[PDB]
Amino acid sequence: HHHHSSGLVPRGSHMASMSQPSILPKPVSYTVGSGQFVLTKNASIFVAGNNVGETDELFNIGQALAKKLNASTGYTISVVKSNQPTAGSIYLTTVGGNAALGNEGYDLITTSNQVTLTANKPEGVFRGNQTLLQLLPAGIEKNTVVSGVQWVIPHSNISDKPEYEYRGLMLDVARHFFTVDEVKRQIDLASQYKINKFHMHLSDDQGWRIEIKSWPDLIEIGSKGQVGGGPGGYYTQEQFKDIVSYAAERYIEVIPEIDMPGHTNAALASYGELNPDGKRKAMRTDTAVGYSTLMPRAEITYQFVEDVISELAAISPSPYIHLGGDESNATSAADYDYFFGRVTAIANSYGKKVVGWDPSDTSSGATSDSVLQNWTCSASTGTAAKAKGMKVIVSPANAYLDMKYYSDSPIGLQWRGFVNTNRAYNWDPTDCIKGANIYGVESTLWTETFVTQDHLDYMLYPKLLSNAEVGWTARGDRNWDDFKERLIEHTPRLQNKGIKFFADPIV
Image (tube, rainbow, N blue to C red; front, side):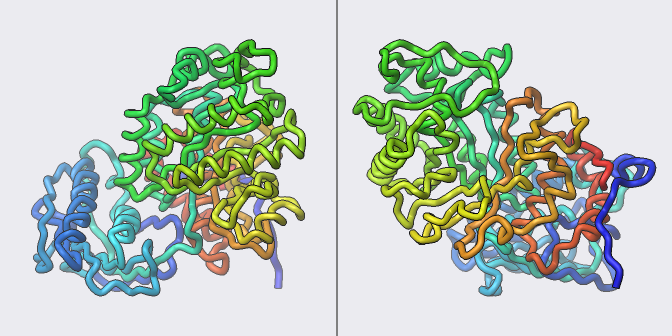
């Protein structure tokens, strides 16, 4: 037999040059029969759970779906609490879910008279609704009313569930600041592709982005810049809670990161007492890394960390707090072991488990409840985590979505090489680490070189779609040639969503 790898498309990207559903990530099974369902102006969404509490949660999910459908159809589809759907209805239910599909899995069966989504949990109804939107014609994902398109769904049968539990996106809001609205939008867009985790990198050398009432100069001084010129910005604790709440409506866990003991210049520029000479650092607007450190052997450091953790824990319902631990090149191995163990103890005392970048798993203060985010992905990375029974989230070069697509990309970095849509697809988490409990995947969007929403869109789309499929779809069902053609077919939907994607010439 003969095989090949993909080159660039002759005459340019098909995402420039280009009944038909466009499901991404690829579901476990999808079959199509004869006939079709038509969504009309008279349609209602019926919801039915196993008890009134569950029905009420499904009702909220139904309303969110109705809002989306109404925006493009111009209909006023309403939601009804009933297990007796009428012909032409969408029906969302958790009664009789296939337990083998787990919390996020679902069956989605469309007949001429009815769309029926059957799940184990409300969460699975939400994930299934992301598929439902992709079964309707391109146009349905428009934010304004679309005319001249019949709103049809083919008679079809889908069963689905994720391969990995953790399928995340990290946004760096320290290097360049993004508004609450911009962050909500990225969360919203990601959710449509079954991303279920949002990691916020809230602090680094060039900025501190979260209000800490006990240390107000973190904002008054530490938030007032960013990479390059800019004014920076920050989230009040109320704005952070708003983001958390918005993500929760999409069954997305928000994991906040306060990076320590490295990547701490913004804190060090806010409070002189955090530095050995007692003087504030100058703010930094360059892109260098590795040079900053908290004082590992000063009690003031641990008081500062405790105050930050106390306040953040109070406003962050996730059982996880990410404490960074990357590129602590100004911290000795001995001090790093000690520091990371001490801050893990503090986090645990406030009821939070710790996530940290490698090599944080090597800290003698880690527990089997701590989680390693393995970004290095080398032969020895996560040896400690594996020995300690720690879950691992993988973020290899293939998940570093801030890398240039190509040598000539107008934005992006390249310290992990180039990452085009193909590279972002052609890997497996088991490639990054062997013999581990792999919790999942996280796409990381660092923002050294991204200033605008358009820059975010350009790098995340279509690259995030590749990573999202690596997280959701089983390896045996993944195939670049298949994904590539599905992605081409999906292009109008990205357009319709107003995503300023890159038309990658490898697609």
